Amino acid sequence: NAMDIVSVALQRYSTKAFDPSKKLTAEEADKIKTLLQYSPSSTNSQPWHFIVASTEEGKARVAKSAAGNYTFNERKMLDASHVVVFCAKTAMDDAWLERVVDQEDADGRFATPEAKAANDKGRRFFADMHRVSLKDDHQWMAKQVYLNVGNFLLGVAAMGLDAVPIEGFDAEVLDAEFGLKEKGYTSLVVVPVGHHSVEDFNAGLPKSRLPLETTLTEV
Amino acid sequence: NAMDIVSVALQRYSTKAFDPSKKLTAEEADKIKTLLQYSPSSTNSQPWHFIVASTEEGKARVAKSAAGNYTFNERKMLDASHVVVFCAKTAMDDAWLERVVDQEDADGRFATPEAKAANDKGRRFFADMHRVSLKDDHQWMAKQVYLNVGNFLLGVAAMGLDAVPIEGFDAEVLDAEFGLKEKGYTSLVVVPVGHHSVEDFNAGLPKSRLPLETTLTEV
Amino acid sequence: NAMDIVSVALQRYSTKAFDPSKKLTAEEADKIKTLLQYSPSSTNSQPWHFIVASTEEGKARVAKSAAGNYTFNERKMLDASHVVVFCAKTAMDDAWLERVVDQEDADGRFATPEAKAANDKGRRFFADMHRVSLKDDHQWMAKQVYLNVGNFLLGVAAMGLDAVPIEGFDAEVLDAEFGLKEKGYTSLVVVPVGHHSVEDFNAGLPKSRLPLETTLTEV
Amino acid sequence: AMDIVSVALQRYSTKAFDPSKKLTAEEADKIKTLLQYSPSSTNSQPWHFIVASTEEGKARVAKSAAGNYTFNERKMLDASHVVVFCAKTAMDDAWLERVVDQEDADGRFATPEAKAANDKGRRFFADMHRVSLKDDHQWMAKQVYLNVGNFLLGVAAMGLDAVPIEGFDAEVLDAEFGLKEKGYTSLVVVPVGHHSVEDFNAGLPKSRLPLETTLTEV
Amino acid sequence: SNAMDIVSVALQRYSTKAFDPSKKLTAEEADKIKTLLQYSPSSTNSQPWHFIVASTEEGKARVAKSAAGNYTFNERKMLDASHVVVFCAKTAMDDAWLERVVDQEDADGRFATPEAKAANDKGRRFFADMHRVSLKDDHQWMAKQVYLNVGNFLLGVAAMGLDAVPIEGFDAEVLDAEFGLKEKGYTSLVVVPVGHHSVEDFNAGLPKSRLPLETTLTEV
Amino acid sequence: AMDIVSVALQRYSTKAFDPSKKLTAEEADKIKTLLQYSPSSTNSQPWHFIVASTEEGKARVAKSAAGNYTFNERKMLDASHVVVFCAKTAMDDAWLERVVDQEDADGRFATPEAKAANDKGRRFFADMHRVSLKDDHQWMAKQVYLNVGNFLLGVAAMGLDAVPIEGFDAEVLDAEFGLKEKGYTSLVVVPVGHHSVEDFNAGLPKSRLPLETTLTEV
Amino acid sequence: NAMDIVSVALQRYSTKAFDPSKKLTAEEADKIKTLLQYSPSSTNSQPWHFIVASTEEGKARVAKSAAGNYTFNERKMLDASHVVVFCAKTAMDDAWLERVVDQEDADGRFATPEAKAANDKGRRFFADMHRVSLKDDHQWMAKQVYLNVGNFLLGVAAMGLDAVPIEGFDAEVLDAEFGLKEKGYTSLVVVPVGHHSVEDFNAGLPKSRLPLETTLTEV
Amino acid sequence: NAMDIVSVALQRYSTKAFDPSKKLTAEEADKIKTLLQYSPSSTNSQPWHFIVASTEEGKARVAKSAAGNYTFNERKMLDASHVVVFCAKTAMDDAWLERVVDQEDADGRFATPEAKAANDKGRRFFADMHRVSLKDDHQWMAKQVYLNVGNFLLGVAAMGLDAVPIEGFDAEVLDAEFGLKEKGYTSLVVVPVGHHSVEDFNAGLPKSRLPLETTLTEV
Ligand SMILES: [Cl-]
Ligand SMILES: [Cl-]
Ligand SMILES: [Cl-]
Ligand SMILES: [Cl-]
Ligand SMILES: [Cl-]
Ligand SMILES: [Cl-]
Ligand SMILES: [Cl-]
Ligand SMILES: [Cl-]
Ligand SMILES: [Cl-]
Ligand SMILES: [Cl-]
Ligand SMILES: [Cl-]
Ligand SMILES: [Cl-]
Ligand code: NA
Ligand code: NA
Ligand code: NA
Ligand code: NA
């Protein structure tokens, strides 16, 4: 019980081994989903999908993505209580842009149709800038997914849970395993969540970061 | 909020109108820098730099990146107490990889020479996959920065501060203003941090997100 | 008249006599009520009441206020088509403050209860400042009434109507005749509206104003 | 023929101004014309205006946006032109003589008696206020608000955005422009220009109490 | 200038129900109202009275404390008026006060001889003893003199263009305590806020009402 | 010229009246108006007045000046008009009704409810005296003195001379006019007229205790 | 009560207000009449008459003389116990001279016929000087009356009574009211006699007389 | 207080012969001066002067006025102890009117300048009425002198002294001998005072006065 978020930031770490017997409570499982849902994103475009594998059969399917050049990650994926796959939309399409603004409307953010149209115009200006002008909407959406991941990592830490972000996995394999390409998504980061085991000596190591003198300019 | 982080996630929003007379305390200024510094990143590569503008002359320089299409963002850059520019490295050089491992060593993460070397090899395994195999290191590093942004936005919300993530600025202009190109960095996101004014009306709107039924698959 | 309003400002004048046979159309009569209603006021507190006299009997009641020392204004009050009495609330009571914000809420200006509450709070702060700290709530509310008068005079001119503000009337008499003080109001300005009589030469006298060299400072 | 009612139904208080949108030279001349040609009791014109259009000028006015009112600073800096409305602090004889002489020079009086009669007629009213009621200061401040009401509807009709600000420190503002010594005090600040795409209020319906409450027809 | 039209003033004054706290008395009006309190006549010129004039915010607040309890409806009138007057009567007609009054009349030069002064004293003491010894009446007798003063005061301040209201609805015990009156030998009787009515006072515009002379007056 | 403090400082108790100087018909009406329009608690008006102006009249009043108050006879006889101030002996319901009904007839009540409330308001105070304190007799008496005070100042302001007399036999006066049965009792006699050149109190200076003693300022 | 006539002279004064309830005793009433009777006068000529009013009806008749300028003297005459009017004869007639000497003869003052006739002649010596030579008997008699008044004022003062000599009355009115002209008299001074009222102003004032250095010469 | 003054009135008589060996004591001589001084007079105007002869030379000067036709009075004037000449003013001058009121003021009879001024007005009224309206101010003043005489004769009788009022002298001679005319006085009555001689048989004669039936009307 605190408001001490910096203590959380200084105490969390990348979990290198989970205790396969320590599970998220029902409520914690609810919270982590809420964290995924409520992350911010450019223009609130929410260009993403999440898979939460919580069953042995589920994590097993996710785990298959580690099979080739990534076997050293398999254990982490199988031992954690919950395993989240962060996926990005493969394209930013009119239908999604409409869905977003229509949801904002249903949530009651526009007092007039003029306000709604101004919101929609603003969003579409940005999105067109990426798909049409810059042709970088793929990496634009991926960046939003990573923003979500940063949010999530701190969020689960604050809940007392352990996690580790994994980029080492065959995305082509994982995508196919869940039919993501057909559905319009591509997997980007996998985050197993649970509690560390006693074999995780990373839990007892000092945190390390480059000094502000290097990474920070005050102006 | 090292506990009830979900309430924080439900209560935060993008501020548009900052009160320019409500500064961060010296304690808070230090904490935000700590959040920047302690963000996770793939292999703890920390491929980033931050500019924190807190003086009027400093904020005005950042604000120049908001000319043209982004004039509406200028006020938030000017009136917020502190303005953070998130920058990514332009290329993952060997020297940066050496610097990260040497720092992990100074901080006491490796009880022996071989533990260090193992860590180094393991980091370069990933670095080379991006630098050599995929040729996507620029994007790879920019995603680390967004993870940082995500971590930051939640952190500052937990500290009771108001913020907004701004993509609406001219990165070219900003880079030139701070000589980032020659320094090896490029700006990606600007985040004004401070306290909202009584006129920041986004504070009176409910949050809107897509339902889980759409964005979440449980297995 | 939307657009060439300056010409309108330079055509209008303070009518000295009205043609008693020229009446506002039913449409014009609505317009003028809209003008009264939709005037701005500090915090939209709308601290006012209007009597619009349009019948022989109604006008004669208002004209009583012109019966002693102000008989030079009696004819304007009797011959004009519609005579409007502008009245200030005699106190900014809690009920009114509540009435105002409930109306804004009904009109859809508040997305959340937090928004309604913040608007209520802010308005109450200002009201209390005038009643309690400054003890100038009467002058404050009378000023909003005069703001309304200004808006009104220009407004009816743009409609092609003649009008004149009258301060030469007995407000004690006029109040008593309508029971204004017991209702929590008091009369401030009377404004006859209609069309000027052929005898009113002033309709084509040159406008006279102090030069800007005297009254305006540009910086 | 207007359509002035639509102007009244479409206008609102702009809270955020686009700092890059300026009045045209012609628009800027017209707002001064509006200020100047506003009505006032006996045409006493008991006022002074400051119009700030430079960044130095608006910054000076903006000092008054301090303490509880810092939230108003940004309006005053971003808007194209910021108008400060000021009332005279006392109705002096010299001003009453100035007005009537200006009317005379403008040819409002066919004869010397017309001038004299106008002068006495104004003094009848002036004296009610400064001798009998001793409220001349409040009386003049009211004329200034009349002007403000005139102005707000004027600029809306020109297609310009605005907002009337009472949340500023009049003492600071008066001192910054040395108004007390000059015989004036500031009352309302009206930033004028074009609203930002992010102006919240432009996205909100207007709200007024219904006529059933505020209007009595007889 | 014009003759004093006092009846005109009687016909215009009224009991003010709402005061404007922005409209203060002038400093000359302040001194004059105190002269009115002083120069009121009284039986035998016995001046059995004390006056509290509250002009400050702290001052009016102390007085307004008397309006708590069953008289909260009088509190606002006591806070909003420029000046508030508390009329108090003496608790006893003591020899000391009799002596004080007769000596003041001497110092003011009303007596040409000791024989004039002594007769004046004897006359006053007769009346006083009749009330305090014989009739057992003195408190009421003195209270009447204070009410006479109030009547003089109400008409007076009206003539000066001021608004006032006589208030009997207040807690005398409390008011006395607040000012340690019992000890000083006085008790509070009437409170009179003085100043100017606000536009909230609709009573200022109401016709005056009085029973017709045909009921209250016998000519003979 | 209306300066009422000047009146206060100039008025005094007249001991000797000029029997040849009468009030004008208009002054007689005016003093009646003063009696009538005096203020009183809740406007309860708990009083009756006898105005003796004939030789026969004043003499009937003068009878109350006997025994110890023989020196007051001449004042009552020599004055133009002699006012006897009387209080009700009891505040009865019928009088309370009469007052409120009169206020109603005079148009002081916008609604039947306003009238009812005025009634309750008065009875709130009446009952505090009638039922609780049991001091209504004295309460009304005090209203009469208020009237006396108002009257003394008024007639002085009219330029008339007067004196408040308590030195008379009230029982005798009451019996002479049948007051007890009518429901009243006499409290104060005030002769009104003009002083004779042998009214020497007119040559004495006024004397009051100093404010230093009688006034607390806060 | 021992005789101290100078005390009486120093204590007496003109009473202005009489107590109407204080009467002379029957004995005092005889005594004041004895005073009037036994006053000296030149040659014992006694050229006088006295009205003594003791009834309300009586004094009212005398008080009529106090009108116009002298109405202020009415209350004295009405309030006093006894009011005395001193009247002088209007001519010295032979019948009166005869009456006086016959009275002296009846009272036993003359031892011989010569004595009586000598006294008669001697009185006429003086009487004729006045009514024949100087032609001033009117004044001469009126002087005797004033002599009587001086005797009287001091006498009643010695009796413990208060009084005042009134010249302020209309003699013509008083004369007519009593049919004095026809009777051969005229009124000169009125002296109310009785007891002062507690409100007699003059009773509390010091006597004032000019100093002897001014009024007296010693040789 | 209640002294037996009537007895004095009934015992006094007009001395016909004085005992030249009997003198007033110094105290008696002070007293009679007081009697002269303290006499009342109309408006206290005190229109008089007194010469008191008590020496052989002084009495002889007064006695010159008895030469010629009045030698029958010579012995009284020479044999008495003190001889008082009563003189009236020849004119009531503003100067005297002023002296009187100023003396009343010095004696402290006036509480305020208002009182003094009224008294001075009242007196001047009366004075003017005599000197101007009636033209009888000589007689008016002479009457006051007689009043004084009457008061004196009873006064001195009460002191146990003998006296006699004398009119039979030559006032022209008496005036001349004391330069009275230039001083503004004229002599009116001479009153020798002392003790009668054994030879004055008149001391024991019955007193004679007309009956009240003739001289007094009671109403
Ligand atoms: Cl679950
Ligand atoms: Cl944010
Ligand atoms: Cl105009
Ligand atoms: Cl000018
Ligand atoms: Cl000027
Ligand atoms: Cl609105
Ligand atoms: Cl609004
Ligand atoms: Cl409506
Ligand atoms: Cl009395
Ligand atoms: Cl005869
Ligand atoms: Cl007289
Ligand atoms: Cl004789
Ligand atoms: Na500029
Ligand atoms: Na719009
Ligand atoms: Na009547
Ligand atoms: Na006769």
Image (spheres, coloured by chain):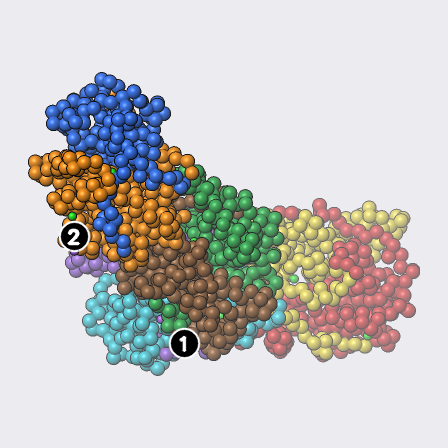
Chain colours: A red, B yellow, C cyan, D purple, E green, F brown, G orange, H blue
Q: Is residue H13 visible?
A: yes
Q: Name the one closer to the observer, E138 or D38.
A: E138
Instruction: Identify the residue at the far left of this view.
Output: G133
Residue E52, percent from left and from top: 52, 50
Q: Is residue E55 visible?
A: no
Q: Which residue is mark 1?
A: F105
H142 over F133 or under it: above or below: above
F6 over G151 or under it: above or below: below
Count every numbered label the image shows and give the total. 2
Q: Residues within 10 Å of mark 1 (few under 14, many from 20)?
A: few
Residue E141, percent from left and from top: 51, 56
Q: Name the one closer to the observer, F185 or E70.
A: F185
- Residue at screen point 30% across, 47% down: G33
Q: Which residue is mark 2?
A: G183
Residue B182, percent from left and from top: 63, 49
Mark 2, ligand 16, within 8 Å: the answer is yes
Give how far apart the Cα atoms at labels 1 and 2 are. 70 Å
Question: Left or right: where does residue A164 sit relative to residue D76?
Answer: right
- Residue at screen point 80% across, 69% down: A28
Residue A67, percent from left and from top: 85, 69
Location of the N terminus of chain B (image quadrant): bottom right
Quadrant in the rendering for residue C62: bottom left
Q: Of the residues shown, which amino acid type is indicated by label 1?
A: Ala
F66 over H189 or under it: above or below: below
